[PDB]
Image (cartoon, rainbow, N blue to C red; front, side, top):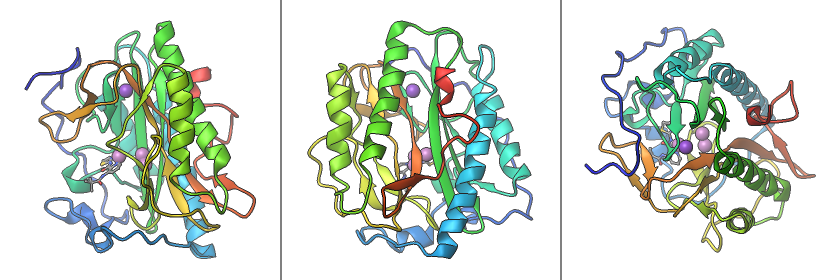
Length: 304
Ligand SMILES: CC(C)(C)C(=O)Nc1cccnc1C(=O)Nc1nccs1
Ligand SMILES: [Co+2]
Ligand SMILES: [Co+2]
Ligand SMILES: [Co+2]
Ligand SMILES: [K+]
């Protein structure tokens, strides 16, 4: 395999971390290939669930807990810390909150969260590589509690970073917030991509096309599929009660992506950097509720 940039996987990975049996597990948790029958039982369907009061309270809770766990990871970002150390803390934080770390064994994903450094677009596997000064790293968190999944992610700076990194991360967050600002009943899901690409393109960046936002609730990934690029064929119209994510991945160079031999790590084909931000949203009558919002601060960690 010909790597696209300077990053390389750092094996071996510590033995799989166990989750106490008292924590409720999703269906794929114990599947040999990590397959989700409940999810596949809807694969291909474009119909979108309309959550009930019970579902909404369930989503508000797991999403709040997921934010708490991302904040734990955020406090560990610094030169010298390995992504595996971050994952360990995330794993323990999920357990402490009586939640199962959704990524664990999801289609056999080996860890409890995704850590994506520099050219890694998404799904980076926490490993033995120490974070280096100047790196940017995204931590994507998803928790499962009482049958519901809560999903969010942020890109962080490791020590001081160059202007290019600052601009990429800042623009990516702005893309996310502009998209969220347009969410309300009646808006087509395909519209978000137009908003995102417009801003990314205006700043000299490209939008990843292989991965999209997604519905989430009793399932980790389900309808609707939400592309982040312009003129897409996304199917569906927003309605009060819908819950989904917007998680744009923006790149310094081209948008082309490819996967590492591990079957998960997605990287830019040109080896340039990529950043991402994500929130789980609940469409309301007046717009939308950002279920994964930070509660003790009006801004994401990178502007600190
Ligand atoms: C079923 C699947 C793994 C092929 C899939 O559609 N998957 C998907 C789509 C869009 C975004 N994200 C994912 C995903 O898995 N994300 C993960 N995060 C942590 C472990 S697996
Ligand atoms: Co994912
Ligand atoms: Co996510
Ligand atoms: Co997501
Ligand atoms: K990255």
